[PDB]
Image: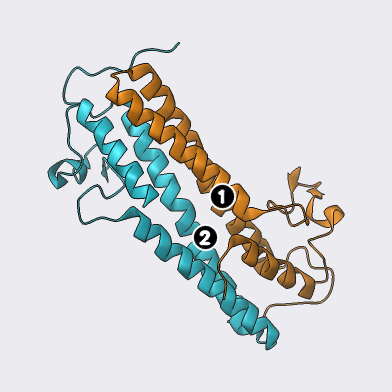
Chain colours: A orange, B cyan
Amino acid sequence: AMETLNDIKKILINVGLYQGFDLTDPKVSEEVNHETANMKWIKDYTSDGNWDNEFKEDLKNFLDYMEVCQLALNDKNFKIASNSLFMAMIYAGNLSLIFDSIKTDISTLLSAEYKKNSFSWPSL
Amino acid sequence: ETLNDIKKILINVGLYQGFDLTDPKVSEEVNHETANMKWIKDYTSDGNWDNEFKEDLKNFLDYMEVCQLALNDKNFKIASNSLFMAMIYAGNLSLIFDSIKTDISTLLSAEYKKNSFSWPSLD
């Protein structure tokens, strides 16, 4: 049963292999698309990557800042409340990005634009 | 229940600006300049932000799992469709946080305050 983001990563690597490439290889997954000046693959597919750790770290930062905001409110310190809300906002954005990034890579696999063989998805 | 905890604090911030987001007359009001609701998230008592997250995540994971099972069976129609639906749910997950981010932004601007509340300038 699929329970973690790292579980999802493994399946995406497998999809890539059907297309003739191995995302766990840094020279594949960390390669720039020279035409667009952007990374071909957004997420880290190398053995050192850990998608669940990225999520938990962003979430903890988000919560921590929200908790500092409430504490500031209780003390009537609206400077710290303001700053803390601002930083929570920043980490909410990071959390959005976690999933947007995965979405983008999935979209890249679905288009098979970087395939190295004759793999083609069936028409639906 | 950590998102629901966050929601409580956001409501508390609103209260200092003189409005109560738990009141649907407040949190569901439309901004007629933008034609959109002033507040994206559901702040009413029946809402459950953690449940929304859990539900989207489960659907995301469920579709990815079907994708892998389809691949093992060399069923690339089902693999394709599952990966597509997983993509849809990854977008929903991104949107959950985007929406919260936006409402936070609305509190930080104090744009909808009902009193003389002002955030201390940090320069």
A67 displayed left or right of B48: right
Residue drawn where x is 47% and y is 68% of the image: B58
Q: Chain of mark 1?
A: A
B92 displayed left or right of A24: left
Task: Residue A26 in the image: state x and y as whole percent.
Answer: 84, 53
Task: Residue B116 in the image: state x and y as whole percent.
Answer: 19, 17
A26 displayed left or right of B23: right
Label 1 residue SS:
helix
Q: Which mark is residue B114?
A: none
Task: Residue B59 in the image: state x and y as whole percent.
Answer: 47, 70
Residues flagged by tags 2 and 1 on a common chain = no
Q: Which mark is residue A55?
A: 1
Q: Report the amino acid beneath label 2.
A: Ala
Q: In front: mark 2 or mark 1?
A: 1
Task: Residue A73 in the image: state x and y as whole percent.
Answer: 30, 25
Q: Report the amino acid beneath label 1.
A: Phe
Q: Which mark is residue B90?
A: 2
